[PDB]
Image (cartoon, rainbow, N blue to C red; front, top):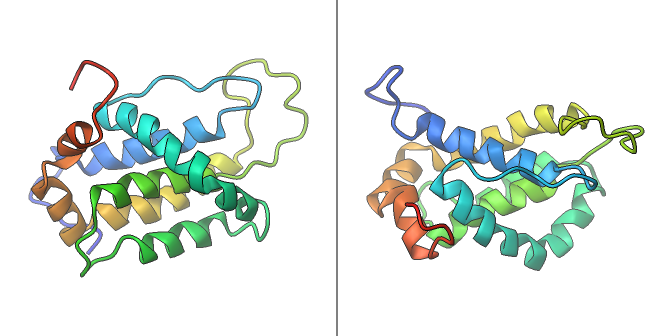
Length: 170
């Protein structure tokens, strides 16, 4: 199941993965006239360094779809089903891949961004699609078997060392 935990408010990575995933979506939608802010955690820093390459390499096709059928979400879940699974021993490479793609689908539909007053300049499509798009992935990895394994291999921590994080921290 996508849910399940022994803690109520003292959740382990529960809000750790959700916040991290959603954080990437915003960074991806980062207005084309304004750079996105820095990461929040180690996974956010490394992922942005590795996941960024996963898109520029694959996004080449993903983007095309992001503005093709508009099913940016339908594709986000579909992919996670091909790479990630429940009875399949996913891999770190698959985890970071989901994050990259997810954000790669993030579509926009503003009006006149030309006038960027602040950094919040963006349609609600990001927040709406961010909840659904991230809701699928977040739960995909935040599952019983998924999460269990994710951490069983060092968790977000093991990934940072696996993909050699750029920042000194973590």
